[PDB]
Length: 188
Image (cartoon, rainbow, N blue to C red; front, side, top):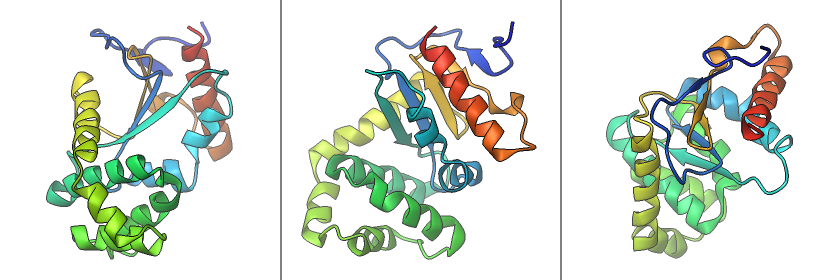
């Protein structure tokens, strides 16, 4: 066929029930994740091609960058709770990988302050049980698919995107193939 299991995607032998429709995993330490966000804009091009009524989920992971990795998973929970994902994603990526100015939880906090989130509001979220459970959800979703690598995308808890099996000679063509594959899987 044109889309084949094991080529543009793989199928989970152990399907995950009740999973988010489109589920994306990343790490601010992850070099292809930086590309996916900054250069390729994968998330946004997938959205542009998803049907009506499909919601999109993005979670951070712990298994890169040790202690800071975990702080970043909690910070991403804060961002989700406050709904400020679109204001902190770029400076977090650049703070970790470009300028390397993020070395502690306090530096992560600085990024939010600079993006205009108020200190009191950040610290209250950071310490909230709503953020605790948001962290729990991120961990659980990644555990459910025994995730050992990022970037990763899963569709309906059953299919996993396989970007190694798409041409990379042209970045635009790669992105559209990726998004079209998500749409195909979505309609499956």
